Structures are given as structure tokens and as C-alpha cells.
Amino acid sequence: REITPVNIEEELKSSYLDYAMSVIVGRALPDVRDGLKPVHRRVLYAMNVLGNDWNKAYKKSARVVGDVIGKYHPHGDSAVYDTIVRMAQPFSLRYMLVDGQGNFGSIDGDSAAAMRYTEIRLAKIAHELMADLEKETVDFVDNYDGTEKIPDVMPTKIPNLLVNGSSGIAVGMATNIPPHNLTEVINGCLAYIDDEDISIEGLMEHIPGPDFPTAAIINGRRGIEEAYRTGRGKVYIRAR
Amino acid sequence: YAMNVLGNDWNKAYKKSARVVGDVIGKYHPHGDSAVYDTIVRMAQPFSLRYMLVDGQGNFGSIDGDSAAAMRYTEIRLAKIAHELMADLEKETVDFVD
Amino acid sequence: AEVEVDAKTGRETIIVHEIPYQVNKARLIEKIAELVKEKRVEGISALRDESDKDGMRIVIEVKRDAVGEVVLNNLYSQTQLQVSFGINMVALHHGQPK
Amino acid sequence: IMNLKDIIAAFVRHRREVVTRRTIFELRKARDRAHILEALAVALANIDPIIELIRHAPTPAEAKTALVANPWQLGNVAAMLERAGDDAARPEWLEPEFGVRDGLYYLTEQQAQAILDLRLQKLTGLEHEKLLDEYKELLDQIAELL
Amino acid sequence: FGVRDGLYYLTEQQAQAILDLRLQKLTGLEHEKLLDEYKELLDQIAELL
Amino acid sequence: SIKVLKGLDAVRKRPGMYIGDTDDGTGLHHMVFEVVDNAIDEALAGHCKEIIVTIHADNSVSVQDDGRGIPTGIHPEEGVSAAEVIMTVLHAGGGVSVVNALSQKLELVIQREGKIHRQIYEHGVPQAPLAVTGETEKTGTMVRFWPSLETFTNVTEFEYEILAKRLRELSFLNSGVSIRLRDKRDGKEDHFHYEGGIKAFVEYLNKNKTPIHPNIFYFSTEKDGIGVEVALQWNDGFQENIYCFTNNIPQRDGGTHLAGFRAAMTRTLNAYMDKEGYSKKAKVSATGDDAREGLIAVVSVKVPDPKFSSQTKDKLVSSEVKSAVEQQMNELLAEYLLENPTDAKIVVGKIIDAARAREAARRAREMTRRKGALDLAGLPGKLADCQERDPALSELYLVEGDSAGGSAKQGRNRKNQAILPLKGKILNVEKARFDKMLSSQEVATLITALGCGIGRDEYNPDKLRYHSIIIMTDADVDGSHIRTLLLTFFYRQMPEIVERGHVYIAQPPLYKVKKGKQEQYIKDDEAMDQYQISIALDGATLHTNASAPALAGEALEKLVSEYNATQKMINRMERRYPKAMLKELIYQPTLTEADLSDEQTVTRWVNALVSELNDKEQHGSQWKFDVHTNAEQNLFEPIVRVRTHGVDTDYPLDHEFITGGEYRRICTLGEKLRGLLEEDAFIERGERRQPVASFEQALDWLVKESRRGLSIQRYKGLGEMNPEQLWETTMDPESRRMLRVTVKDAIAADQLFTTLMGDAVEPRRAFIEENALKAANIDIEN
Ligand SMILES: [Mg+2]
């Protein structure tokens, strides 16, 4: 009735398992098909719906953040703006997805301006990740209030996960993937389509290793093969 | 005017305050957003206006000095008497500016 | 405000129902407490707030050798139980102040 | 925990699924458009009886329910309809008692409704030729998709 | 333009409106609706004047 | 007439889905109760309003009334008497026809207009048209039926007490109706006739007990389409018994017509006791539980269109009954108390005795010092302290932030409730050091507010200032994380507080759903699914053919629940088999284990399955089959091959799959589902009508129909709720639900805390993988 006894172990286990599963499945790890976290996909879809194309006028960041918060993402607005800022920095992504106007920080440590100053619009390559979206190529799900529809995965023509990488922290596990080069990945995909039985050594003839936006020098060739063969490895980067 | 354009009528569902603030800032008001939100809050308190113009949902402060919640929690919509201030707006009764 | 007298003991208290426009209740209570602490107003023993869903209710208790009306007048004179409002009607007419 | 080959294979599988679904969607849309175009083209060969039937009707519902009462002769569209081989352009949800049965056409409710929404400017022959051009293009697209 | 002597003269927009007429407008019931609207329009014009 | 044969055959094929269980002995009495309900509804306008129920020696039952007879006219469009139409026809889509169909012989006698009529039915088929036998001068109707021996097994004899209880209750509820129950096998008679109504009901219940006051409270009014009747009395026991009814249908779980009763009683008793000065003379304060000891009451309402939680009633959820009961109770109980002083004195004496008895079950609690206007007492500035000085009658609430803090402060009870806000996520003391914990600010504020000390050197558990600590966070996952952190802190630093039982957990809601003028609060997703299912089936009837009575609500609900469970089980195993293939095995004949070493049957079975799969394909897949020969046990395992997206895959159905529990559950569902709907089956909900061809189509149509006009509201935090809602949902002591934390085993708790909140990662990852990734494929299906 009003008061009901409960054991502490059951409550602790249930609450912690719920939180851990929610964090693992919906906040920190990317998908293997498009390489996007839910926030990135929701931001891209919201920008697409507004018709903020790559050959039109800019729009203020506050409007986009407000739309995203009010229709798809039930969280705070500072995190969304911080996520948007990172997708427009040339020194953070190998291929930027957002085109920006204003002060978006610097490699020297300067912070970006407030969201009441900047303007954004979609990049040209970002349209290739949402091609044929209106021809029933993917599934749709409901939002938190059950009044909208959100794509479950993007029908991309670009292997975004390898070319842009990922990084995140979760409960009990973490991820770290470096970026690569587009032409080499395309050649590797063509070779796989041709053979579908090619070994790891055959694939490395087209993809020698990673490629960083800041150039520099990779010292040593070991670690790359181990990472490509098993999934874990360590490499060294040296300045010029 | 922004709330009227959004179609946020008095007999429909509420909308998030952040969306309205973003629309106002991005299309009509070239200033900050905190001041706009504070202005929106005052038009919904029963102890500040004799006839309120905005209907609110959530914590909007009290007369004891409590502050209103952040704009990521509350929801608003137009009041019934507010529709009388914008009647016959589409029949060329006033002038328009850029 | 008014004064209520106990039937048996004869003790009298002051009950406040409403406050002037644009006045904070917490600041008023703090000001009264500060005045009592520094011994600038005499004849106050207890002070607490009992406002609930029914309405506002502030209780002030006087000492054994004090008159409630004198204390009420002193509170009127020194605290924000009475305030002044200055009317100044200025508006834009044909784009000009008037 | 994955390696390079798994990621490449997953990307290829995703591409295959996307292309298949897109092709199915396009085929369905093309078949529906061709089905509408056939009924639109048939009505232009019997303009006078249709006009008389519509004029004598007191209510549009009565005209709609009287349109699907008797078969209509093909006339000049027999050669156009002969090009459609078997059921290439036939929608998959269409019952066998409709369409061309024996030198005659049997309309449905949707086709009858489509006729009542025809502008008076469609009686020009230019639109008549446009119908044939669109029909041929739709047939070619259906063949390619199949 | 308009009625001059037992005859009617049309304009470009009036001719354009004729070409955009649906076939269902030839039904008997649809014809009588125009005459109903004409009287209401005349009454509204009189009241506004 | 052939349609009547189809209807009767449809009823007789599956009797259990129309009348109830057929072996325990429930429908055997449900038929009699249905006939009696029809008779009592009809005979309400009779001159004497008398009903006679007789049990004969040849195991038959007859019901007779004295009202106006059933009309004996002839329908122009049917050519038959109206009585036959009533007894046979379904009366369009959406209760005597079932009884006629399930009885091997029924005799009907109708007398009106100075004539006597008679007809005989055999298995629902009339033997002759209605005929006149004689002339009379009275009116009435008699129905006598012999239950069929081909459908009712095990218990096949009527009882006497089961009928007696229900008939007595019906006589109590319907004032002015006389019911006689006669028996012939042994010889017994009874006569139920009470004009008092609910007062006699209360007297009957409170008979073997000892009442303490002579008078009985009673009233009966009607505000707007709603009628309320209440009667209550006090005895000298220590029990509570309240009986609720709605349109003569009992509810065992209460509803909206009980909360108003309880609240009104509490308010009226507290107000009277405070005004009369009885509380001041004593040194105790009463509560709701003390008032409701040794109490017997009956509540009955009349509502035009009631709404319940499920199809088995047991709970009322109509939102406009609570105020109707509460206002009348508040208005009239004070008047009752004012007129009779002796009963008031006795009742308040008993309540005071109980309240004082409660007080003697506490410990020694010295008085505390409360923060006030004239004294801060060195307490944190964010605390909103109460006015009660006794720690045993005080509560403390912990909230996440300032918005929730303000929302709770605006809707609390200032007398004995306090609020203390926090700031975001708190430090994890399991991974931190003692000096780091001391240097924190939120922990220091919490320690100062508790006032017990820290470090286990000056930490005295007897200095606690509040004997009730309540954790109230948001309803999302971050609230759960913060709750775990707070529990870790309390267990690791102050074990004695948890051991004594001073920690509670609150349960605020997450969703609010509104449809029309109906409102309701939803806690989590499971309640959301239950609400969707409940509102989908309200006012819906299913007919298996053109002319057949609609199925019972309970059977339809059970079928829906079983189908949903099977669908969830199928969805949980999509990684190993195609879902389309699994969904098709429900409608295919079961493949027994014996039919595996014989061959020539597996081939036909798989061929039929593949043909059916290829018939309904709409995504471009192609299905082919193969048969595998085993040389060990001479078995024959089916093989299914498919090609999707240009990729060939093979799925073999081996011996293990056949004997598994998943296929057993699928076959169990199929046995009920197979062959149910005939060709001309139709569904309807209210006024809309829709022909259907499959169960899934009808279910989807009902779900789509039920969602029109529905509104859903989600609360991100407590700052999104109005103060009154938060009060009435979580903070009101009369209408709140909470939990008390206890410890079962110390070793297990310590190990679990170390594993989950510790620094090492590998044990935590292993635990998460074992509990979450695995143990979800439950292969029990039982
Ligand atoms: Mg929150």
C-alpha cells in the first residue's frame, strides 16, 4: 500500500543495469553502417527538413538548436551546440559535414563564439549521406512524445566510419578509431566486390594506413597490421 | 506575431519555449535570448499582469522570490484574450515593414 | 492587516492578508526580522509565515506590555507595508514622446 | 570488436539492401501511373457519350456509379494497348475481372473518379500525343526495372 | 467589356477560368449552386455599401 | 432460416469462448445468473415485482416473473413472432441466445392479453410455431431449460449457496423487489425482501460483531446523472471492510469512488476534533489509519457510461466520480456529527485511544532546533525547514536542482515537511578518498543538514533530526544513476540509518494521457502498453461469421495477451531465423516428432509451407525447399532455402527445434487461432463497421481507431509539473506510494557494491555482459 519493503540489492541492480544499458545502446557508441551517433543523425535530419542546403543563405545556430531540442532531442541545448561546433572544425574532421560562418575556435586553444553570433548550413558532401531518403529505403521510429518520425539509419553512399573515425566513453567499454583517405577506401571496396575472398594482406595493398587532418609523420609500421588483423593496436605519431 | 505565425493557438498542445525563442531570435529580434525568455516569463505571471497574455505549463516563479525554471523545461501557448489583439490581421488593416 | 485578541489570556496578534503591488514577501520578512534584531522596533515576540493553498497568512505576536495599534503604525511608517506609487504617463504619439 | 573486412562487408550489404528497396518503390509507382494513364487515354475516344451521360446525371455520385455500368469500346487505342505485353504494366492488386477482357474495357471506381476531374483544356490533341509519349516512356522504365 | 446589348464580352482571365472547368461541373446539381452564391454576393455588396 | 443453423453451430463449436469455463462449474451458474438478470431488468415495472427461482429434481431450473410479457407480434419483414426473433436472431452486431444454443431443451410460456402462449426449442431449433393453449387473466413469463450434457462435464449439479449469496446481494441493491428461492431435491425456502436497502446491508454484515453506537449514517442523492449511496457504522474490532459497487457490479480493487470517501472522512473527522478541542486536551494527533479501524461501509454509484481498467471490471477509472462523492460526504458528515453528540464522543474516544496506542511504540527523541526567521541556527541557506520540533513527526525531501526545488516548495505542507536541493551528479565515494570526500561542498551541506556527524568518531546516530528521509529524483535514467549514488553514500558512510529504516524512495510519474474528458497518470512503458491495450478493446465486438453472437470480452483479452507474448518471443529470436517464416508456422499444421522417420509427409508439409510463403511475398524474395536424409536414426529433417538481395541462405529445421519450447508455444497459440474466423467475419467498435479477413488486420484496425484524439505529455523533470499535480501525485500522505529500504544479506550486498561501484572494470563488464546481453533469450515458454 502506502509503504512497501524492498531489498537494497534488487533496487541497486535494476537501476544500474537500466542506466548502463541506456548509455551503452543510445548515447556513446556509433553504428557500423553509417558511423553516426544518434545526436549527429538527429541534427542532420533536422537541418535537412528545414531546407538548409549547401547553395542557399545561412541560418542562425539558435534556430536550429531550438528546433532540434523542441522536436527530436529531449536534452540540454549546450551539448547540442558543442556537438555542432565540432563538426565544422577543419582540424577535427577529415571531411567536414557542416559549413560555418564566424569564429569556430582555433588549434591554439581559443573557444568558439556564443550561438547568438554564428551561422551554419549543410556541406556539399553531407547531401550524399541522405540520398534517396524519400523512397522508403530505411525504417522510421517515433519521437519521445509520439508526434514525429525519425529515420533509424541513413542511406549513405559514403563509408563515413572509416573516413571520419569515432571516439566515445561508455560504461565498461570505450572506442577509438582513426580517420582514413576516401580514394583508398573506395579502391578497397571495389577490390572486395571483385573478390569477396581477399585476405587482410591483399586489402592492405590499397589501404596502407590512417591519414590525419594535421599531416605529421607516423613512426613505425607495426601496430597497424595488428590493429587491422585483430582490432587493437598502438601507433606513434611524430612531428615534422 | 511569431507565436501567431507558428500556429500556437489557445486550444491546442503546448510547445517548448526554446523553439519560440529560437524563432524570435533568428527571424525578427537581433538581440540576445535570455532577455527574450525573461520577457516571455513576465507575461504569464498572474501577479504581474491584470490580464495575462500567455498560458504557461510548469514552474514560472512565485511571489516569495522564487525564480522560474530554465527554458529547457517549460511550455507555453497563447491565451484566449490574446486572439482579440490580432483580429482581422490578414485583411489589410495595418502596415508592414521589413 | 488587523488585530485579533484572545478571549481568555487577552494576548493579541497581528494577521496580514494582502501586500502592496510589486513587493517581495521574503525581503519584507527579512527586513522586519532585521529591525527587531537591532532593537529599533519594540513590542514583537514571535514572527512566522503560515501561507498555504487557502491564501496568504503572516502572524506577528506582541509582548505583554505593548499595544498592537502602535506597533502596526510603526510597521506602516518604517517597513514596506505602505509604499508610494508615482504616476507618470508617457507614450509615443505619431512617433513622438508626449 | 571488428576488423576491416567486417566493416567493408557490412557497407556492401547495406548498399545492396538500399538499392533493392529503391527499385521496388520505383516499380510500384510506375505501374500505378501507367494504370491511371490507360483510363485517361480511353475516355478521349468516347467524348460525346460520356458528356451526354454526365449531363443527364443529377448528382456526381450518380454519374460515377453510372460510368462503371457498361464496357467501353477501345476504338483507336487498341494498337496502343497491344504494345503492353502480358501483365507488365498491370498493378499487382488488380482483380482479374477488370481491364481489357474482349475488345472492351472495364473501368474501376478510382479510374471513374479520375475521369470526372479532367480539365476542358485536355481536349487538345497535343495532350493526346503527350499521353502516348508518357506511356511509352513508362513501358521502357518498367522493362528496365524488371 | 461585360453586357452591352443582349451580348456578353469576355476578358482574358475569364476565358482562362473557362478552360479550367472540371467535367463534374456539368452535373445538374452543380449548376444551381452558382445562382445561390450570386444573391448572397449581391446582398453582401449592398450591406458593405 | 439457414443462417440460424450457422450461428448455432458456431456457438456450439467453441462453447468455452462464449459462456466461460465448462469443467469447474462457472458457466453452469452464469447462464442462470444471465437469465435472472434479464428477468429482474424486465420485471422492474411489475405490480408486485416478484421473482421465483426453482431447482427441480430432474436437474432443471425455471425463472418466473410477473411483469409485462414479451411481445407476441409478427415482424412484417420476418414473418415470425417477435419471441422467436429475440430467442434466435443476433439483433445486429454488438443474452438468451447463447443459453438457448447451449441447452438441449428449452420451454417458453408467455401469457398476456388474456391468452396463454407456449413454444418448445430443441438444441435451438423450434419444433412448432407459437400457439395459443388457453385464456388467462394475468401477465408473466417463464423460462425452463435443461443444460446440455455434451458440453458441461465434471460438475453438473447446481448448488444452493452460490445462488443465495448473489440473490441476497441483488435484493439488497434493488430496493422493493422480492426474490424467492425454492428447492425440491431436499426442500428449502428463502425470502429476500428488504425496503431499507443499504442500511439492511450494513446491519447484516455487522451482526456477529459488536457495534458501539446505535445510529447508522446514511444518505442518498443525485447531482447530475450520478447517484451516490453510502452507509457506515463502527464496531469494536481492529479491521477495515469497505464494499464498492458500480451498476450492481462489485469492484475488488476500489477505484475513483473510494479515494473521495477516504479523503472526506479524514477531513471531516480532523476538522471536528480540532474544533471541539479534544486534540488540544490530549497530546496526540490522529491520522487516516486510526480513524478507519473497526469500520464497515458500503458505497454504490450509478453512472451512464462507466470506464474500467480492464475487461474484468475490478477497478473504476472514471475521473468525474471522485468529486461527486467527496463533496456530498463533506457536506453531510458534519451535519450527522452535529446532531448526535453521544456517537461522536464514543468515536472520538476510540480514535484517541488508538492514536495514543500508536505513540507508545517509538523511541526516546529529544527535541531539535528549527531554522526560523529570528534564528538561522547555522544551517544551510538552501534549506526550507519545517515548523515541527519533534523529529519523529518530520520528513526531509532531496531533489536534483533549483527548478524542482521551487516546484516542490510551492506545493508542500509547511508544517512538517522540508526541502533540500542539490546540484547535479554527486561525488562517487567508492572511488574517492576520505579527504577528497571531506573537501566536497554538496556532501558537506548534506552532512550539516542531517546533523549526525561524520568519520565514525563523533558520528552519533542518535542525533538524527528527521526520522524519515525520502529520495525524490526525476523519472528518467539519470534519476536512477543519482539514486544509486545516494544509496552508495548512505550504505558506505551511515549504515545505522539504513539498518533502523529511515530511508524511503518516492515514485513520481513519467507520462500523462488525456482523451476527451478522461485523464490518467502513467508510470513507465509497461503501464503505457497496458493502457493502449485497454483503450483499444473498449466497446469492441467480433463476429466470426455473418450471423453469430459476439465473443466475450475476457476471451478476446486473453487471446490478445497471448498473441502479444508470442509476438515478443518471436521478435527476440529474429537473429537465427527469418521472421516471415516464423510468423507462418502458426497457421500450419503441427509437425509431430513421430512424423519425422516416416518420410512422404515432411515433403508435403514443407512444399505447402514454401508455396504459402511464395504466394504472399511482396519484397522480391524466392523460397525453395529440400529434404535431408539422416542415416543414424533414419530421420528426415526439413530444409528451407531463401534468396534475399541476391544472397542465398539455408535454414535447417533439425530435431532439436521440433522438440523445443518455442515451437511448442507457437503450436499452442496456433491451436486456438487456426480455423477461427470464417469467410464473412466483421469487426466493429462503437458505430464504425469494418469487414476483416485476419486477426492481425482487425487488431491493427482497432489500434489505429483507438488513437484518435489522444494526447500524450512527457515530464523531463519535476520543474515541468505544476505544484498541485506534484502534491496530489507524490506528496499527499493519503494518495502516495513509497518503498522502505531493508538489507537481507550483508555479504552479498557488500560484494555487489564492490563489484558495481568499484574501480576495477573487468568484473563490471563481465557482470553487465552476463546479466544484460545473456539471460534475455528465455527458452522456457512456461
Ligand atoms: Mg532531467
Image (cartoon, rainbow, N blue to C red):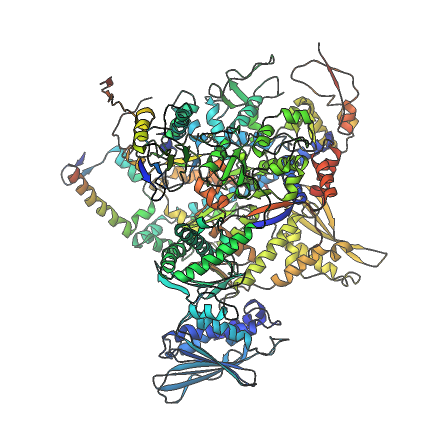
Left or right, F352 with respect to F426, comes to left
Left or right, D6 with respect to E44, comes to right
Q: Which residue ends up furthest to the bottom in the rendered image?
A: F134
Q: Which residue ends up furthest to the left in the rendered image?
A: E5
Q: Give the answer, above or below, for where D10 lies relative to A100.
A: below
Q: Give the answer, above or below, for where F102 lies relative to D73.
A: below
> Is residue F1 shown to the viewer in this render?
yes
Q: Which residue ends up furthest to the front in the rendered image?
A: C65
> Is residue F580 shown to the viewer in this render?
no
Q: Position of residue F147 (x, y in %)?
A: 56, 79
Q: Where on the image, by quarter, is ligand 1?
A: top right
Q: Position of residue F655 (x, y in %)?
A: 78, 56
Q: Quadrant of residue F92?
A: bottom left
Query: In the image shown, does A55 or F487 lie closer to the viewer?
Result: F487
Q: Which residue ends up furthest to the right in the rendered image?
A: F632
Query: In the image shown, does A211 or F641 lie closer to the viewer?
Result: A211
